[PDB]
Image (spheres, grey):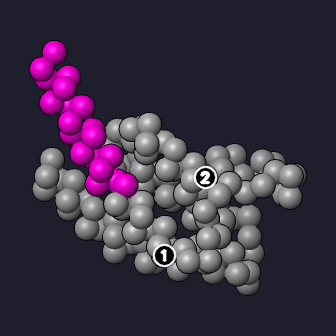
Amino acid sequence: SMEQVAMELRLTELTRLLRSVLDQLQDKDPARIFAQPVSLKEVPDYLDHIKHPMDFATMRKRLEAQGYKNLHEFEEDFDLIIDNCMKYNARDTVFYRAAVRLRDQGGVVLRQARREVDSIG
């Protein structure tokens, strides 16, 4: 159908907007603390602590499979990156601190993306 294609152009454009959002969020992590999944070789107990691991490469794979239906699903995954870190790591660690800074700085980007998603539909 013609509608399914119209829809697919929207999802494709959402994917386009979310790609740019993902790039902006990832720039707020210059130390690359959140770039890749926590290694289960190097933290073998990790899944005993954290039930839904997340990281920027894993989000990117989902994005490129147009696996995000709306901004809310994308935000959910960003929030997991931050929240998982703030649980596993103590307050006085470079890792916890990095998550706080990413949350704070990401807020601004996510604020405008919500307005852009509502505005452009």
Can you give x and y, in whole percent of width and height, for residue 76 in the image? 47, 51
- Look at 62% across and 77% down and name the residue there: 31
In the foreground, 106 or 25? 25
Can you give x and y, in whole percent of width and height, for residue 35 in the image? 60, 62
Q: Which residue is mark 2?
A: 54
Q: Is residue 3 above or below residue 20?
A: above
Can you give x and y, in whole percent of width and height, for residue 111 in the image? 29, 68
Looking at the rendered structure, the secondary structure element under dot 2 is loop
The secondary structure making up most of the magenta span is: helix
Answer left or right for 19 relative to 98: left
Q: Is residue 17 covered in magenta?
A: yes
Q: Which residue is mark 1?
A: 28
Answer left or right for 49 relative to 118: right
Q: Name the quadrant of the N terminus.
A: top left
Q: Is residue 93 above or below residue 22?
A: below
Q: Is residue 101 above or below residue 47?
A: below
Report whether residue 100 is seen.
no
- What label sits on residue 86 in the rendered view? none
- Look at 39% across and 38% down and name the residue there: 66
